[PDB]
Length: 187
Ligand code: HEM
Image 1: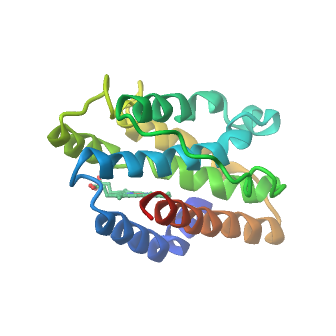
Image 2: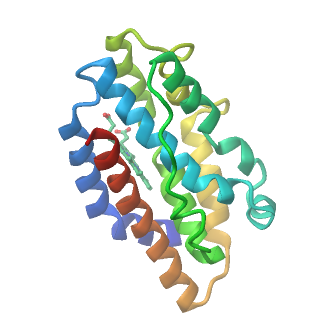
Image 3: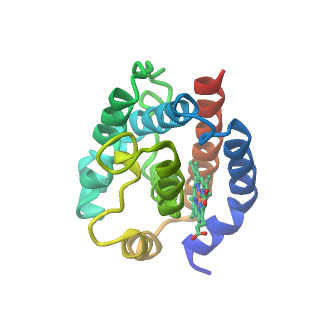
């Protein structure tokens, strides 16, 4: 019924595939490997920037701007001595509909879930919230409620059937994009 639940079903496979891809790149084998993972996160933030700063979406999601993680990820790349990668502008210039944008935000916000596990694994590489893993630090209100607050708004929006299709497309496209970014930074 809820939009969030439908999106969860629709992206269950892409998620399993993505989780497997991440495990295969061995992000915690070394700081260099971890840095390549941070580079992928950083590039995904560049794709999402125009959405987190969009006035229309900011009105729908109060506090939107502060959900971005670009400064932290860029600071982490600097800590790790990894040069910042160049964004290809493909998503920023894609001219996404509002509905597609909701699917991209769904995936970006959802990608924060379980980050405490990644944060814990980063400790093995002697990294933490003040060095190298700044982008995985837990948010103020806590990961849980941050997600619950976002989903309540998402599920309340009224969309027509075409817009629902576009939101699903946006979520699918975002999962595929993160995978492309990982293949790029680990190449
Ligand atoms: C770019 C997309 C995403 C990436 C890169 C991603 C990656 C991951 C990874 C690698 C893990 C395993 C963490 C660990 O090592 O323990 C994971 C766990 C998880 N992901 Fe995602 N994810 C993404 C999007 C999403 C979305 C959209 C949702 C939800 C709508 C989601 C929900 C979860 C949850 C619930 C867990 C398990 C958390 C727990 O066990 O407490 N993820 N994800």
